[PDB]
Length: 315
Image (cartoon, rainbow, N blue to C red; front, side):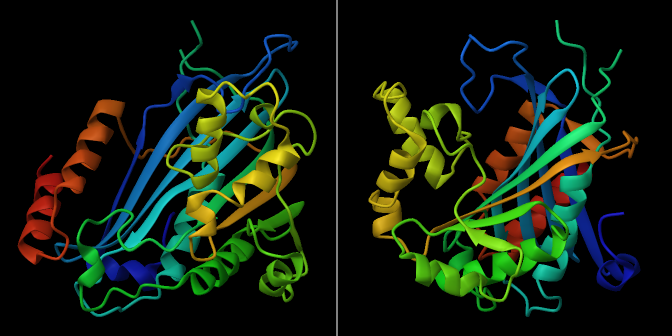
């Protein structure tokens, strides 16, 4: 179950939660055609929101990518959006919801994956990669929420400390926990993790070779935007991993940004058991339609928010 009783309180709070139907996509990491037994990539979108009566309290969007090899899965979990509304005074600490929900999504293994041109059975060996960027945004998910009376907007260093604390609490025992703050000197980065014995400076991806063959291109990710540029300018053949991260630090989004940071955690060789857990699943089009409706709601206006929620409850 996603959230403990002390938070839902038998219907005082309600959840929206749904996944897309698992969909094959091209690998977000460039695979040379040379490769012997290239993986299939399956992507699942997860959307979560917490409701209080008919108002949205917070939202979380997470993309899961399964790189399916013959004997194992490389499973990337990418936090796409995390935001609060702030129309009402804060009753629960946001981290005590985001933490458990994100852990639920990381560990979820009930996907109904169709065969590549009955359902496919996944290898039991999974290698987990959790990828989070931290960037202080006023309204990542909820348009016009930034000037709601009870929206607490963290500055970049405070937001990073918050994410490190959440992520540390749901990756206990993982093989590594990496923090990079592009453009920051190493001792400034080390200060954020000095109390976290399992964390180190750097990143989780392959360290050598071409950047595009090591670093996943996630949608709406500051790292991804630079990768996109490298690819569209067809410099994918020259840009190394080390040079990519060096130049990432000078992008406008980082150099003009407020402590824009990159977190990655890995757990290697986890044996998992595939277990059905019936949740609402929707087509990509239904998912996008929901997100497009969300984009048009004035989240400073309780009427529009209530209407959006009742329309979702309706169907």
